[PDB]
Amino acid sequence: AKIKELMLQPERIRNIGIAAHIDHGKTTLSDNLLAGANAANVSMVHNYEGKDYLINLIDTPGHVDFGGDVTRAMRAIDGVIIVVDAVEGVMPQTETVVRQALREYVKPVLFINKVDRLIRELKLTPQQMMERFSKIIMDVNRLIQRYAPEEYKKKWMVKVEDGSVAFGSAYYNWALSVPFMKRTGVKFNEIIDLTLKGDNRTLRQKAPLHVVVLDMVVRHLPSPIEAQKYRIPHLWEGDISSDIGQAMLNCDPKGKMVMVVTKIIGEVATGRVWSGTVKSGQEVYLINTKRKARIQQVGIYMGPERINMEAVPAGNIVAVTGLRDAMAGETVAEEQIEPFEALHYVSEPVVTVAIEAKNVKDLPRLIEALRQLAKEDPTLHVKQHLLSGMGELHLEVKLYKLKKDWGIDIEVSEPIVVYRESITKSSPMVEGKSPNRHNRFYIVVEPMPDEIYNAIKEGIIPEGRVKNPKEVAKKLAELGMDYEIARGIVDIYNGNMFIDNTKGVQYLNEVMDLLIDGFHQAMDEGPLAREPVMKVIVRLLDAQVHEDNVHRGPAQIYPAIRTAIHCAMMKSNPVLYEPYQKVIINIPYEYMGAVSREITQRRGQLVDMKQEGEVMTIIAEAPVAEMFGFAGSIRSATSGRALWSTEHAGFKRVPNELAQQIIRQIRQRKGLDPNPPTEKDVCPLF
């Protein structure tokens, strides 16, 4: 409860993360650091030279092929503990995360781990071990000299002599730095002795891990109020001279409250309070998702657990509940400000994989273990059954958690790409008759103009049955559409729309709901390959509808409008669309040529290219179908130094020379007649 005494003082806060190479001592270090006094945040109170401090250990992923996570995490912290394995030394993955910390103006401190190996396995002398440390330190300081902001290329360098380097063993719970040696008296030659005779418990208290490392933390990693003076200008795109800008610049609880969301686990959003003061029952603007909401329960962290609190000021790490669907990275503020991150594309599942248990035993909580990942991850959809997500790696993570963590031996099919269908020309008028031949509909389908589709995808024109027809009609006419036709707008559905341009059709109003259901069925599965349809306009030109509902069931109306739509589409040059990924790659400049080649080899294109000193951020787009194995390729092409990630970037038309074989595969896979249908197969004779 001394936490509340501490949160009011920015200069007493340490917002930090741990960057460790896969198996260099990360979770071990985190765990034993807390015990020494996936989690979004874990906090620690630490006494240093009389005063107490509150240190926030924020989750900081280091999977270089999930760049998005690494980058976001770095943006949240002011200081990072680089952890390097004494034996193994500075690894390529370690260089990459360090690079990201430096890019996001995060000050580094070093912890050389697994020294216990140096002592027991190799029987090194103190002299030899200190020299080993010096090459590790030299390697790290080459990274800082190369990639740190120019202001800090020398300042941010780490040195054992001032205690911006410590060394020890996370596992065996001990660490040393020279400033700890001179306020305690201990030397390194005893720790060697204590290690070699096996006196683990005396080692543990004569040179304690948490004491030495957190000393380094407090002494050398900045507080929010210190760091936000140089970090906010690099993090935020708005007017710094403004007053929301100055409120974040200085670490300001005076001001209007502004926070960023770091992670989401009811739903719980962890976040960092840049300026102002968060409060329970606080109304806020969610800047990217462009909606509004109210903060229900606020809390602060005590180690792993969240303890309810409500008025907690700038500089702190917060948990809040009931923030709607705001995803990690969103800017939350009492005002409307320029967001820290830009709006991200919507995301839809585009790869699917077939999974089963190869031991027919573990199945029913394999089926729990399936919608269990769907529990925690909305972007994961499960139907065997089928796993559908955002890409190869997104799925693989799940497949990794099922075999190892949930202990299931599993068979896994080759991945399948999810395609879509559209058309490229307008159709002639087509008639659908119900089977009983008492209801008739006359339609055309037209290619939907890009400007209208985009307007639908980005919310300007809402999905669903159209509540305000004359308003939407006017918006459509603002876009390219003929206003009079536009007024017949009825439904918008998954990137398509249905339009009624009939006049004086008695009882049309009795069947309109069924026509829309049938419309939806027609878009659910297109005529080329039963893939979902996008970018089609259906227009109802005319119709004859029976007086009496006994002659108008679903069984009459559905097949009439469904077959009409599909036949018409077949007459309009039906085509396949395929999903693309936006590819965000971070590399040392020397690899620029190689990476470009790699993107071009997968039918991709460079979109953008940003440069900062010796580092390079490139943005590309490539077909999901061409991106399998990309981690492998970009790894060797960069000697493990690429940081990268992907986002959904919508759908584009499949090139004509690739399409027929892809259609054939999809139809074969679905147990259909392999031939791409033609209008002769879908439309009825004479």
Image (tube, rainbow, N blue to C red):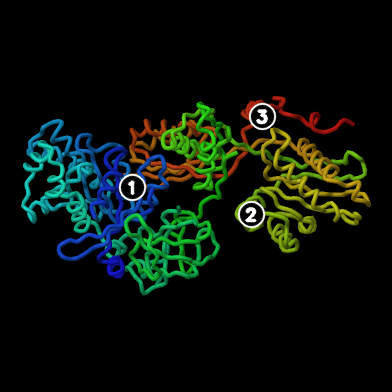
Q: Residue at x 12, y 41 (%)?
A: 199
Residue in front for this viewpoint, 127 or 482: 127
Q: Nearer the viewer, mark 2 or mark 1?
A: 1
Separation (CA) of disc 2 from disc 1: 35 Å
Front-most of residues 227 and 118: 118
Where residue 382 appears, x then y in whole percent?
A: 57, 40
Q: CA distance from mark 1 to mark 3?
A: 44 Å
Q: Nearer the viewer, mark 1 or mark 3?
A: 3
| Residue on which the image places disc 3 | 670
Residue 241 visible, this orientation: no
Left/right of residue 625 with respect to residue 20 in the rendered view: right
Q: Is residue 302 visible?
A: yes
Q: CA distance from mark 3 to mark 2?
A: 33 Å
**Quarter of the picture holding the N terminus:** bottom left
Q: Earlier in the sequence, mark 3 or mark 2?
A: 2
Binning the other alpha carbons within 10 Å of mark 3 as few (below 14), some (14 to 19) or many (20 upward) gives few
- Judged by depth in the image, the label closer to the viewer, 3 or 2, is 3
Q: Residue furthest bottom?
A: 254
Query: Which structural element holds mark 1?
Result: helix
Q: Amino acid at mark 3?
A: Lys
Residue 533, horizontal then vertical, whole percent = 68, 41
Circle 3/circle 2 CB separation < 8 Å:
no
Can you say whether 352 is above or below 508 in the image?
above
Examine the rendered structure and indicate whether residue 631 appears above or below residue 62. above
Q: Secondary structure at mark 3?
A: loop
Q: Amino acid at mark 1?
A: Gln
Query: In which image quadrant can residue 316 be found?
Result: bottom left
Which residue is tagged 2?
Answer: 455
Mark with earlier residue (2, 1): 1
Mark 1, residue position: 100
Q: Is residue 285 left or right of residue 199?
A: right
